[PDB]
Amino acid sequence: CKSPGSSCSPTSYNCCRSCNPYTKRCY
Image (cartoon, rainbow, N blue to C red; front, top):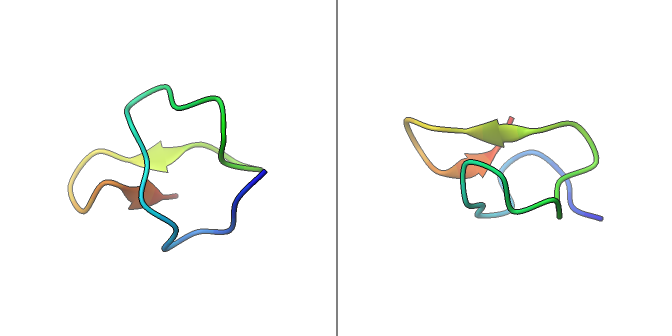
């Protein structure tokens, strides 16, 4: 999975925590 700051999709299902809809970085 990814770290915060990694770039995500609202639900990439690739962030170890979630995404940040206002950066599009993992939360």
